[PDB]
Length: 48
Length: 48
Image (cartoon, rainbow over all chains, first blue to last red; front, side, top):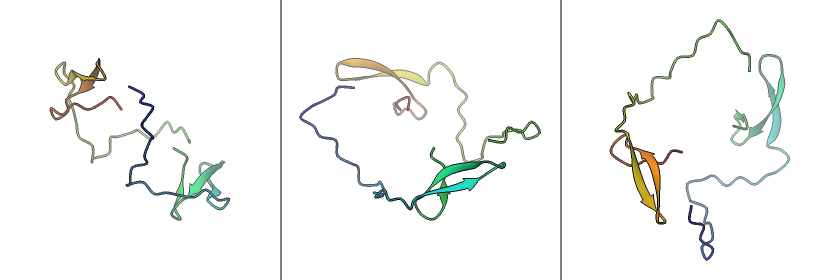
């Protein structure tokens, strides 16, 4: 609440800053369906 | 996915338990308004 204006949102430091390139978007399967996931650190991560 | 009927969900172990009672919720103020929050440890914790 209380939407200031003079204030600009600053990104907190403890967040990995990932550039988005067309390499992090791969697929995996589970229960015989092909979903889309991320490759942020080698491990396939679902979008949630 | 894979909505099983045999498998039953169990709470993972590393999760605090809170037997909810009507004292764990309380109010906190900000921006000249009021809001409802939790008191899991006396510390007012927002709902999210």
